[PDB]
Image (tube, coloured by chain):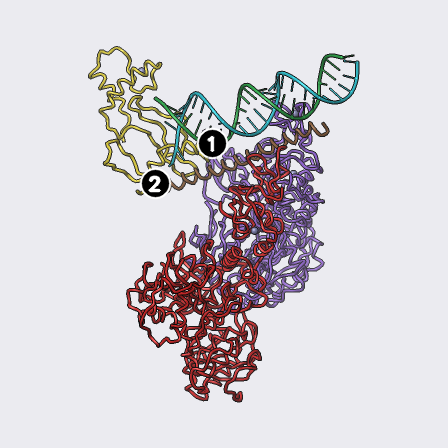
Chain colours: A brown, B purple, C red, D yellow, E green, F cyan
Amino acid sequence: RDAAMQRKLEKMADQAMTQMYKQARSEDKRAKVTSAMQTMLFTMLRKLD
Amino acid sequence: AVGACVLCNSQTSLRCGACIRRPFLCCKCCYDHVISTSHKLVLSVNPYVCNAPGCDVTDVTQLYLGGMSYYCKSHKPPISFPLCANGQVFGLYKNTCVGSDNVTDFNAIATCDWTNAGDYILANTCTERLKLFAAETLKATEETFKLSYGIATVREVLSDRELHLSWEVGKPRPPLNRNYVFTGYRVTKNSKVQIGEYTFEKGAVVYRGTTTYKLNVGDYFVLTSHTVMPLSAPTLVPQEHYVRITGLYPTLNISDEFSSNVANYQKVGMQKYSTLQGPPGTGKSHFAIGLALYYPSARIVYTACSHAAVDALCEKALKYLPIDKCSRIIPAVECFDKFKVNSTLEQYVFCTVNALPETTADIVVFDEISMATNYDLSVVNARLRAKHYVYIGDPAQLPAPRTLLTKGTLEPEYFNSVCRLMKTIGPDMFLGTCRRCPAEIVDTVSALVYDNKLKAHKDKSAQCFKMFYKGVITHDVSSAINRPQIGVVREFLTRNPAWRKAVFISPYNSQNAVASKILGLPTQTVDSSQGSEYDYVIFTQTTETAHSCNVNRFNVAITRAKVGILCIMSDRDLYDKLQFTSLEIP
Amino acid sequence: VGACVLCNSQTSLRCGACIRRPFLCCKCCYDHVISTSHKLVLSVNPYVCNAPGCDVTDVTQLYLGGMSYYCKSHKPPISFPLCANGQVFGLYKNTCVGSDNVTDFNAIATCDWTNAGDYILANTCTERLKLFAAETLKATEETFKLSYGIATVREVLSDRELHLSWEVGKPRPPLNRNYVFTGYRVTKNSKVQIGEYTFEKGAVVYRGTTTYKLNVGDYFVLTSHTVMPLSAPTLVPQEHYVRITGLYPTLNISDEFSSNVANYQKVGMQKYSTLQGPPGTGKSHFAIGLALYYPSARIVYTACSHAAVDALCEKALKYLPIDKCSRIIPAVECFDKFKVNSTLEQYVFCTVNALPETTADIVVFDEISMATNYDLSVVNARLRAKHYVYIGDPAQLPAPRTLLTKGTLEPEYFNSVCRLMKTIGPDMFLGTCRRCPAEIVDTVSALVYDNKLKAHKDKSAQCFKMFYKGVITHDVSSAINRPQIGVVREFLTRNPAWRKAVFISPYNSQNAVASKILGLPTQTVDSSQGSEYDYVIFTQTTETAHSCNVNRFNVAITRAKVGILCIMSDRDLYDKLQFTSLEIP
Amino acid sequence: LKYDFTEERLKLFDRYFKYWDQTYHPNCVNCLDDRCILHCANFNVLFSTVFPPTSFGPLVRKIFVDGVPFVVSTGYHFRELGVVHNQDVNLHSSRLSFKELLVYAADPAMHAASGNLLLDKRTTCFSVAALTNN
RNA sequence: GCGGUAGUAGCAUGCUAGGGAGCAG
RNA sequence: UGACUGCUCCCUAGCAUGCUACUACCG
Ligand SMILES: [Zn+2]
Ligand SMILES: [Zn+2]
Ligand SMILES: [Zn+2]
Ligand SMILES: [Zn+2]
Ligand SMILES: [Zn+2]
């Protein structure tokens, strides 16, 4: 196993790193959509007369 | 969520948790930071702590990767994988890691609690993202400083200019004067509204509110704080001197009121930045207004530490320039308001480091370089990427009040990254046009620090004074009161009633809170003084300590006189130099 | 998904690091990838490690995950290296033939176009190499022009002058009108409508083609287009028919062009003929003679410009009825006597710019030397005709090579057909020297022209010889010399009848200095042929390889009907020229 | 501006169904179970054909968030359920969360208040607004 | 001669996930 | 510009489990 159960970690580490890659993206898309929603609100109120 | 680390500039996702400002750190580079400190908590997209329900462990190497989680050994599943290993802590981009062999520079800044002058020798003699981290750490820990103190409850009100005031429990007390200006706000039944800008001094509580208001019961004050967010541009760009002043507009006609000015501007358009040797009242406020006419086509960036300092830049603003071409952004503070306000796309935009918005302009002119540090130094360039740059002022007039520096005060010379430059590269400009003080004081300040450099203005009418005294001082809370010299003050001020047409100068301005009741004489703040002055100023230095008679602090107080200041130099610090009229002490 | 260049087998890979990204064949693509840094290859999807957020992009650096391509740092246990077997993994992996020596192809691809060796490659290559080469030149040069600042007119002083700066960090475009800008103006948001401009010695002298008056913030750059690939060859595999069948033998003829009819007769017995066309040898007259000889021809008049086909349309309606001519001018102000926007037209003149694609009768191409292999294949990609003719001569004028640095390329390999009249020989010739007399013509015949062009007329001793030196001192993108400019009036003074001439000069800013001294008009050296006076004053103002090389201002000497001026400060060809010499005052 | 119509519904009930011996809650918020809701919404269905159709739909209100005035929906006036008021409405809010940004971008209040009036004569359904120019 | 564990490959079933599609109200 | 459900087929991946064979160690 000094070569065949660890190799199984070179699996788990890869998977965990991929998952947290994905979650970092998912948290950047969130901030982007938040900026978008709030700038829409603040640009549509200024029409309010 | 994910950026480039300081010590590496590789793209990382790890922020030192125990570290104050939490900068992005690179895997190998983060490990180097974690191996030498107690900064032993690191946050990635999620914090690296054992998420077994209700645990305690929070050191990084203390944890192992348990699948979807991070655990301690007391929790780790049989299949684990230590997070901190391989000489490289586990995070995103684990391949692109370069580190620095000696990061104890970085750890030293991070483990710097800012007590000694060594701390600011670190803050300057560091490297760069170190420099912004340093300035920002100073600010952060000092706005955390101010609020370790009580809530200033005005709980009875007696008279005007006086309050009955207590504070919260367990906390020491903020000092006596207005570098620590409060900004309290009032409640109703539920939450917290408006009061204003206040400070409390020797009463009985003397409050000097900037705006008009009358206070009630339960009225409380604290030094309300903000959120110092990080800083981008460098303190100063990697500058260089052009080959011709191309892109800049050579004008035909000139005003020789400032003949000490035009030869000074000509290469400034042939160069990125010039910080000038600006001795007090050497037409420095006049200086930047001369180029205003020389290059009236310049979107020239007038900035200072305040619209009490850029106030001086706006002093002769419309007096020299047409009106609608000046503007200042005052955010939602009462100072100068002759201009049109809230117009950034303006030909001449004056402002303070507080709130001029971010644009691109022509030539920067920065008043107040000594007292401002590396933080707001990078602010104007983070504000603005201009044609060229100028800093007006001088490390030869004052530093900032260092709330946490405790051992010996730092050099005049390392005030900031550019302040060393006129002491390691030399002065980029100079102005010896002494329109203010005469042969009285000026060269005696030239034989002081100024290179034997500033000539006489005028005759020496023997009006700035010498008195060789001693005095007796006793201490209190955050001041020092001495009347053996205060007794000398009227004793000085009496033998000619023409004496007392002067402004009292004094370090421990409560010593004027005792003097104002004796004389009626106005007050002079020692450090917030330059720009303001009379020909006649009475000064009781009332202390000889490192607080007091150090080289360049009340240096700003001696040069206040057009012709006639008073100096009861109870110090042997620099008295061995000063060349003025001496008399017997009655 | 098409056929690869070096193989013509149907492939799906396109070299990614390569500039123009041609289709490459699996084995053939591997051959290209083994010898360059062109180490990125795109198939239907790009061959790069799609593990979330990686860096690796070399091809052999990757292995076939299943639905993906990974590096070793990402590859799943079950992998399969993409680049192996001597054959890179793509569609049609079976039909791959390659070429044993493709360093021809790699050499074109790794060619950054600096030396004349680059264009020796561009011509002495093989075919789809040839179109790839010309198209690579164009691509990298329209990428060239925009490495430069945005020409902001940021103050306006007077007319014919501007206050103008540019963007940051960029060097500056040169001085004259081979690099014509076409700026466009903004409002608050986006970019709309200025025009065609160029900036010269002022103070910024702008020579706008159309009428307009500029404001503040007004900016200019050399707006670019998208060079899309070519199709037809530069020239078909041609052959000479057995009789001029399908072509219409006419009974009557005009012997104004008796130097013409024996020239056309076999041209209908043949696909293409490029003609030896010396300057003003009735070459513009030549193609108009066949116009009457075969008035039944849909004959394809094309040139490098409606400043050059302008000359083809000079005697157009003067010789042909009106409604049978037409020129397509796309949405540029030049000739507009014709009906415009009519391709189905008996006579269609145009430029390589925008004559649409049809099939016609006999091609007649002005400007063959300055145009290269790109637009050479354009007219045949435009048009598959009966037969072909190219008017002009490599004995005129090449193109301005923006990237050629070391040692200008031969007159002889201007293009694939230009070698032919130097390796096969001239298909036609015209020695009908209607223009210059015995003065200059044979002295240009003993130059490069085979001792071939006869005298027109007497030798009135009006083209001139001056043995001088001058002193030159440089600036941005010009060269200014007044020891010869001082000679100019010094030449021009002793008879005020001198100065009824057009100034010739290489560094046309040297006329921006001369025009204020004389009032004399300007002559561009290279954009000159077709235009001329009997009287032209010329200060060559330089003897360098820019200057007194064999066949550049060759076009400037032959401008005179009878009387040009040549202050030959050069020892380059002065050892030849047989004209009136005087002392230098 | 009137939207309540609670007294009018009671006067109608008392004018026409005087001896119907079961409690009628004009606003079904006060109902006791789902059968009482059905009972009283039945009557609201009838009595709402009398009142003007512009008085149904969200009841907006000018709130102040970051010192700036929004117009947001703090209730509703159903034809079947009467007037319903939101319970957690707050006027001076410092900044919005993700959830509040959501529930404010979804309301038709800010959208309709900031659009052109619309008179669409192709249909008979009560048009409200035109969020565009064409 | 048996048991056991460990490995590896083959094979199957199932569950989850990802993708492509079809029908229905 | 693409709604809410339900069912079904196909392809891939993962994991465990389950089944079978080959090899190894020890009892
Ligand atoms: Zn730290
Ligand atoms: Zn734990
Ligand atoms: Zn390539
Ligand atoms: Zn990879
Ligand atoms: Zn009910």
Secondary structure category for the residue under label 1? loop
SS of the residue at dot 2? loop
Q: Chain of mark 2?
A: A
The circle drawn on residue B485 is none
Vertical relation: C253 (above or below) B301 = below
B498 over B55 or under it: above or below: below
Give coordinates of residue B51: x percent, y percent: 61, 26
Snapshot quadrant of residue C247: bottom left
B21 up-or-down from B539: above or below: above
Give the x, y percent position of residue B361: 50, 56
Which chain letter matches label 1?
Answer: B
Respond yes or no on whether mark 2 lies under 8 Å from ligand 5.
Answer: no
Query: Label 1 belongs to which residue?
Result: B191
| Tag nearer the camera, 1 or 2 | 2
Q: Which image quadrant is residue C105 in?
A: bottom right
The picture places residue C552, in percent across and down from the top left corner, at: 51, 73
- What amino acid type is highlighted by mark number 2? Leu
Local packing at callout 2 (Cα closer than 10 Å; few below 14, some 14-19, many 20+) is: some
* Left-right relation of D6 to B550: left
Answer few, some or many: residues within 10 Å of disc 1's Cα (few below 14, many 20 plus, some between 14 and 19).
few
Residue at which label 2 appears: A48
Q: Residue at x 49, y 45 (%)?
A: C1
Q: Please, what is the three-letter code of the amino acid marked with disc 1? A: Ser
Residue B136 appearing in the image = no
Nearest the eye: D58 or D8: D58
Same chain check for tags 1 and 2: no
The part of the image, by quadrant, that contains residue F14 is: top right
Marks 1 and 2, how far apart at CA: 30 Å
Viewed as shown, does residue B578 lie left or right of C53? Answer: right
User: Farthest residue in the left direction?
Assistant: D15
Q: Is mark 1 within 8 Å of ligand 1?
A: no
